[PDB]
Length: 56
Image (cartoon, rainbow, N blue to C red):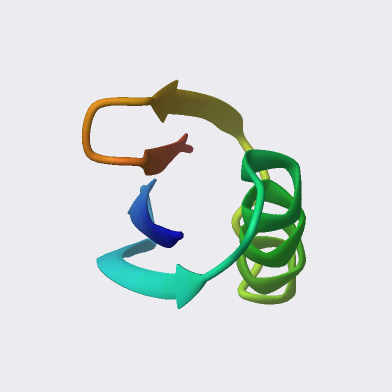
């Protein structure tokens, strides 16, 4: 499934996508990516457009 990520951090914003099977896998991928980008905040999920938003 095509999963989207919205980085809404005070010092890092943007949007990216990944081909992930399950929501858990998608969140794991984005979790590693975001955390490696230094963005660890609140994680919101929208099931309409398959989008995770990280609020920092």
